[PDB]
Amino acid sequence: APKVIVFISGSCLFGAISRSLFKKLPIPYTVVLLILGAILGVVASNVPLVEEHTRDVAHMDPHVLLQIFLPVLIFESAFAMDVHTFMRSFSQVCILALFGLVVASVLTAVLAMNLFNYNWNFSEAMMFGAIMSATDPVAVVALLKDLGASKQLGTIIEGESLLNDGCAIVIFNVFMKMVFFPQLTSTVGQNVLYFLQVAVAGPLWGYAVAKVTVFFLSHIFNDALVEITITLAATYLTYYIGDIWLEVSGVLAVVVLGLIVNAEKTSISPEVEVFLHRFWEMLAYLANTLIFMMVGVVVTQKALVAVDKMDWFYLIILYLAITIIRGMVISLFSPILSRIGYGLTWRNAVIMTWGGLRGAVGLALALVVENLAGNDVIGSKFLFHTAGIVVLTLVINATTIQTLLRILGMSDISIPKRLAMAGAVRRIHEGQNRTLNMLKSDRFLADADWDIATAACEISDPYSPREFADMMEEARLRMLKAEKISYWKQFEHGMLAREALRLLVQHAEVAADEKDQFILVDDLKKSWQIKGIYPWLKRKLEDLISLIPKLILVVNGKINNQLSLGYDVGKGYIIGEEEVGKIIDRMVDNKKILRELKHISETGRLQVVKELGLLQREHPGIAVSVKTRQAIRTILNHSRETIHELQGAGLLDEMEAHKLELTVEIKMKRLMNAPSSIPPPPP
Amino acid sequence: APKVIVFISGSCLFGAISRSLFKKLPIPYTVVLLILGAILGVVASNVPLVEEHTRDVAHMDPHVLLQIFLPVLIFESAFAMDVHTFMRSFSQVCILALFGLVVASVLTAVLAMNLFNYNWNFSEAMMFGAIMSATDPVAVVALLKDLGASKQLGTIIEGESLLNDGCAIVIFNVFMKMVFFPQLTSTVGQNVLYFLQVAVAGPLWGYAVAKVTVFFLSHIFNDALVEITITLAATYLTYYIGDIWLEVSGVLAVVVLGLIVNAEKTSISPEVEVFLHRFWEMLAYLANTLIFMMVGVVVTQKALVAVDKMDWFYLIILYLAITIIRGMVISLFSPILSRIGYGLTWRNAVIMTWGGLRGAVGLALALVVENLAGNDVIGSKFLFHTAGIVVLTLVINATTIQTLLRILGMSDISIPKRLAMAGAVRRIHEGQNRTLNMLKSDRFLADADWDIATAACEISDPYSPREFADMMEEARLRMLKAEKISYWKQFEHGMLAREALRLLVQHAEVAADEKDQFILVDDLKKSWQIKGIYPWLKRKLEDLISLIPKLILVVNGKINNQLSLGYDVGKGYIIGEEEVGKIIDRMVDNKKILRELKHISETGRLQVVKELGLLQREHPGIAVSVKTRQAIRTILNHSRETIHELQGAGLLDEMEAHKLELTVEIKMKRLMNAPSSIPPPPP
């Protein structure tokens, strides 16, 4: 009879209670989860049966808890990313994560040696800084995505969290294997070979197993269960094979596996995408709950017997030191991120310094370094410092980050957003009023109550000369709002891709950020440009042909992936300009500015149609293949709507319409692995 | 560095390979999974590394594998049921499962005693029968659900599998505690006390923890992870507490918990319903794969060293004898089951006879016996017999049940559903042709390929005087087909409950199976039958009043659910008669039979209207509450459609529309937890 099952179920029930009872309060559920873990630990210190449960579960081996709890949390943090905005901002995020992590660990080691009274070494203080610098701000990025326009800020803080966490586990692991396993004395060349093979074969093995997983997932139809099992087995086997069967740090392998799988899901069916997102979020929630309750039990059992007032004072100075260190790192690396196309303002820098929340990854590393130390006091000091810093950072930084988001003025509602929200509230009020008026003249519902129905069905708003040049700017902003709604309408019909929609709306908003310019061509130059090493290798392999067919198929697939996005962007621009020229007459009443804006739209139309013609001429087979792909996708979606309205006509039951939906889903998954470039037909 | 993770990942990959590769073959994936497990066990018998992995995993404690695997499989087998058709046939399937299981275990014990050469006593042979009588026909249930109108017998065999697993593991645990732990000698009074305590406090504890879990799930809004966590923790804690902390039969507790939670999902949000269904199916697949692979490994490592030709002959005649015994059980219990409302015909009798497929439940119990027997030969003979029965039963019974459903004529597709399918194929073909002609005249995809796209867009055929009185019967069948089409069309609008729609279509099909009678009111008046013990309890407690407030609230909620079901059935019949009277003119040309059929429909409508008037006379306030619920549901559904059409018009962005959808989903869940009877207002 195991006690792991009853401890896991009790931790799950306590986590459910902490999530339910602490929704409105700004203190997160993990703090009261750690408090309940401390209460459970002192109950185990009194009661022998709870002592049996806690010695069965909480006093476990570090390696099994590491290799179980890190893959699920790391894969969820890499699978919840938005890969397009992360990859288009990978430069500043990657250099900030790597350089800020190494200099923050160095500064934390130096300040630990200059402040603490323990007789530690430089490598052990570097290990302590590696544990300290690990972050996991789920609540910060949730609040940042709840305030609207800072989507890029949430993207860069999530990418900083993922890369900082992964490489923090990497540096903690290499210093743990250097210090805690001291029987190996090696040369400089073998050490730099080991560092090179870790830092290369992490993402390399992760990319190899990710492409193997993608190749497996693409050729699977009509069973989501195999896809879920293959994803879970690939993640766990990747981490275990990397971390045990070779010497490669497998953390980066799981990070890049999650990033590549998130760059996929075109192959994965959408119901499996929704299931995998919810399933990995649930697994990470269970892992966080188990890690927090285990570290609460172990902290109140064995880390409480050595704490004194000097340790408390060093903990307070440690909190101030890590805040000052993160502020200094961001302030020192601010010109480097300002040198790139997306710089950061001072409010984003402040909310990134205050956005650092210590995480269950750091608690798991603290548990590993606590149990791996033995009976000496150093592991208890590491665990106590990590628990104190995570409690202080979680409570104070959560409450003050809500306060600072309110104060710094980026949480306010936008005036066109507020107007659109008020219009939607008025529209749903009129819709409910006419629904009530229709329900009044019902032969079954004329006797029904209406005051209770109106009280229940009420939705409140959650958000509570030179003049001629000024109205030119107002007409321009109304025109770009019409552009936004036209782009969203053509996205809604299924004619556009999600990434092309995101590119169009980011081009429209950076056009909106200026005074008297529309969505131009110079910001749209980089859309369809396949220019680079790809056509160079394409013409190299075409000269060599006339594994080489596999290489030219891979190059053709990359060219198809760029060209479909460029084709979608150009055709979406055509559709948007045609629609906004259809509706230019209603909103614009002045003929001069009407002809001016129509001339601007016609110039954009002619340049985009000639560049689309040149795009077709430069690669005929690729263009005809992607337009055949768009045609077959359109007619498959029309057949899907035909099946849906046949179910909505009552002529076909749910089971046979489900069979036909399965047939057209098989057809769309077969359309996913289409041939890359059909040859052009003879006349 | 555990090896359970690498064996779990390897088993998951092997199960994925076996499911993907053998999809077209009629051989199930479990047999080739066990073959791969046997090959891996032979490799472990040779290679020391695979020996270490199989020693770490396959040589596990039986109690930990029981309490890990059995609640998952039992809860998924309970949760995958449709609870309405299970509860309507609960008496028949309960007496069939219980009596057939006990007499099959007795006959298998007697057969083993007079057949096998071992000196087994009666209790070990009863344990052998309890292992041998456990059935898991999942693929049979899927095949019967594929075969059209065989819904009732599929639900009967599914509930038979669930209850057979339940009391089979109950009697297995009782006789295993009798044999393998014989140090306790007990009195007859204490033995019957233990039997009554098990057979009562199993379902009692299951019902108590199920109502606690349901009341917890009803008060949880806008988060899913808490609900998934609560469901999984409730299942694990229920099985562990019942098996260990009490002497409760833990299998029956999880059966009752799964059936009660399946009676709900009115409280659970629909996305959480879909996630819970797919997640429990995935957990059951993982448990089944692990059980089959470990069974193959142990049965080729330690349970194949005592095999001989006499053992093989005994196994073959054991298979023949248990097939004969199950057929004899079905034949002898056919009249008792035929006295009830759904009598089993001989084709359904031999389908349920040949449908008995042994599986993971019996394999896990055989593993428990093989580990508990130690070095004795009894565990080896048990595991070899059970594994051989499972593999040959799966192969032979799967192939012969495919040929049996072909031979018996239950795989024959009905002529009107084939005509409707052909009409749907014609409609989707002409829709494909007209949208192809629409795609012909466009400025975007004019240069695209056409022949390959049209070849890929082919939804093919999946299915490849007195006579004047006889054509009146066909017109009656056509008009009841129109009535059930109207019922499904009312279901499309969102006025009918799922159980009300199922009741209407089963009334429609039992009217279709008769000569000259329509969907009458005599078979329809069972829906609102309030004549029961609940109004008697309500009136006696109201006379006591004028904890019992909670009692009358529970009784009021139960009769509120009954009144809601009856009112939905009556209103659905009224709206269906109004619709079929609106469309009676087109499909009827003869005026005399037109007036006759319209008179029948009008008399039925008047009868239903007057008895619903009597029904709302009986309980005014509960009728007010249910029509208030109907009005609130209609207004919120129109609000959801208004948000969806603001999204479809592009006026509202995706995240604010998701926030509004979350708001109306919260209001719908609050409508689910409404007061069951609002008091009527004074005039």
Image: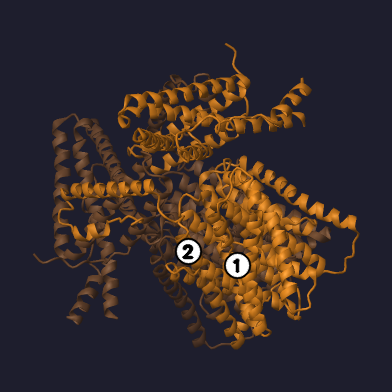
Chain colours: A orange, B brown
Task: Determine the residue positioned at 50% across, 22% down.
Answer: B445
> Dot 2: few (<14), some (14–19), or many (≥20) neighbours within 10 Å?
some
Q: For mark 1, give the secondary structure.
A: helix
* Left or right, residue B104 beside residue B413: right
Rendering coords of residue B71 (x, y %): 54, 66
Q: Which residue is mark 2?
A: A402
The reply, left or right, for residue A508 in relation to residue A363 is left
Residue A431 location in percent, x, y? 26, 47
Chain bearing tag 1 is B
Mark identifier at residue B68: 1
Locate the N terminus of chain A by quadrant: bottom right
Which residue occupies 77% across, 64% down? B306
Quarter of the image holding residue B624? bottom left
A381 lies above or below B603: below
- Which amino acid is tagged 1? Ile
Residue A73, placed above or below residue B189: above
Q: Amino acid at mark 2?
A: Gln
Q: CA distance from mark 1 to mark 2?
A: 42 Å
Specify whether residue A265 is in view. yes
Residue B290, label in figure: none
**For the point 26% across and 56% down, which residue is it?**
B632
Task: Give percent across and percent down for residue A554.
Answer: 69, 33
Rendered residue at 36%/55% (across/down): A463
Q: What chain does badge 2 belong to? A: A
SS category of the residue bearing label 2 = helix
Q: Quick one: B173 or A375, which is closer to the camera? A: A375
